[PDB]
Length: 155
Length: 155
Ligand SMILES: [Cu+2]
Ligand SMILES: [Cu+2]
Ligand SMILES: [Cu+2]
Ligand SMILES: [Cu+2]
Ligand SMILES: [Zn+2]
Ligand SMILES: [Zn+2]
Image (cartoon, rainbow over the protein chains, first blue to last red):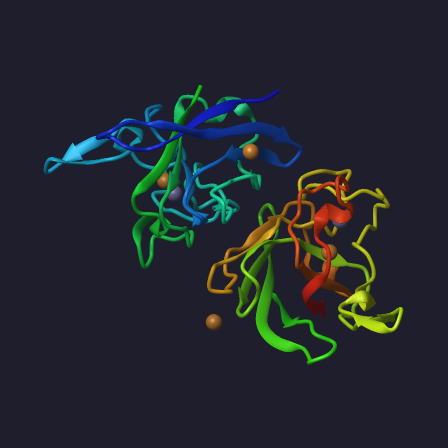
């Protein structure tokens, strides 16, 4: 009847810290992602489900870049393109952008109409990027979210 | 096909300001509302379809109140409750909250899964509130939206 994702802000060098959680429920129109995050940068952020059920980084050129353990966006239907949460051409893991209040709190729930059961999302990660999401691979790849600001494993 | 709603920032004393449009299109999972608004107050705002095809103010106790001519939330199924966009117990006009960037712009689209055809929404109004939306009538009625900030007639 529910799923509570332990969301933590990413940081390879010093350490991961718990920013709150995200509960995933089923509605008659798809999975609902309701967060109770506190202490994040304000604004709209890219919100997507990734491949590997891990939130640990991967260094490159010495410079460790957070969240790479998660891999790319979850794409079991191999569309090979980033898009809208309501488009069949998009990665199945593409969710609506997440809003973080002026006080760093995320409490506005979003719907992923293409996901029906809680089981589908298990064994994958939940990523929250630094930038937004224009739901296209242009002008920037993967909606332009960029650096991975927060993450959590869906168990 | 597409419906282009001309939206105005409401001000009965100084005069309304043209702030952009909201395009309504049909997706495989419901109606998509794509804004391109400018000059609005930043933050998360209540976003709903109201009964009457009007954005006119009405006088109440000596002063004009912005947008009262739009009537209440569109409720064809007569649920009598304000709720979530994915709940069948909520007014059919209940849409996901609209995010306005720190620069006053709104460009992030939202989905109303319970609405399927463009014609359904014609003959009504699209309202953007000063306050937010918790998708319940408690603690504040109609999700806590409060005053009517911007509005457009759906033709
Ligand atoms: Cu809290
Ligand atoms: Cu991502
Ligand atoms: Cu513009
Ligand atoms: Cu309203
Ligand atoms: Zn994607
Ligand atoms: Zn309502």
